[PDB]
Image 1: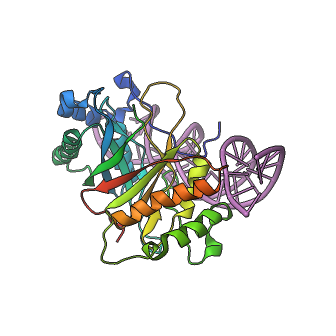
Image 2 (image 1 turned 90 degrees about the horizontal axis):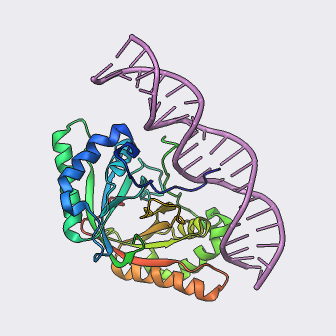
Image 3 (image 1 turned 90 degrees about the vertical axis):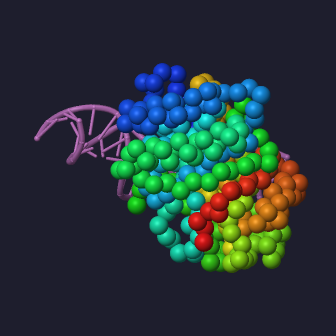
Length: 137
Length: 137
DNA sequence: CCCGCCCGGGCATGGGGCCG
DNA sequence: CGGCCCCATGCCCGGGCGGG
């Protein structure tokens, strides 16, 4: 068909479903998150980490990399550009989490990835709280 | 620059610049937000309201309508869909705000519009908090 | 007046995959 | 290997329709 609007990243069953160039980051996060990456039925989706920066390509790899039961990235999006001026675009990715601890852990995971991979770009991040749970079931 | 990644909606100098379909909501929101729509240079961008639903077109109208000094919508994006199945995509729009009062007002403003216009679709929403301020200057 | 839902066109890729 | 490439791709515009 004809896409007019963004589509959600498709979830993985096999590691093959994850695009090859993003596989190491993905694997890293798995090992990093451990049990915290599995879906916990009792938790509801109230948290996120927003990652942002000027490079959409790296952000896409990050989005492709965080896909798990309890940690799910949305697609690459962007922030409003502040000036009435059209400025350098600031891209972002929301990584949704089922609790606060996991979101902090997610932040730190990406930091450690950057530490091990100098050529990866340095992303800004912030913890996000939602008053009401998101329909991520 | 980066045609395959999303672009931040463009600001309006005057009301004629607002795309036609979004213009009624835009007018209404302007009047409802009142002084709170103007930028307060002391405030930092720590809040948002996320609106979500299944109509990307409705959400596009909302995104275009909320563009002000202190209220700035991002583009139409979507949430991850939890199951590895075919389920309706849930689209969303983050509307960024310079303080908490204003975000409450934004939430309310859309509720009012929906109350005046029963043909309009009912958007779910939540207030959103950031630990660190966003680079909306 | 405004609603949801529909459609075609156009840009400049940029990332999966080949080859040096 | 890992740097490089090129056309399937991801994005956005804006008009239109029948209806309440």
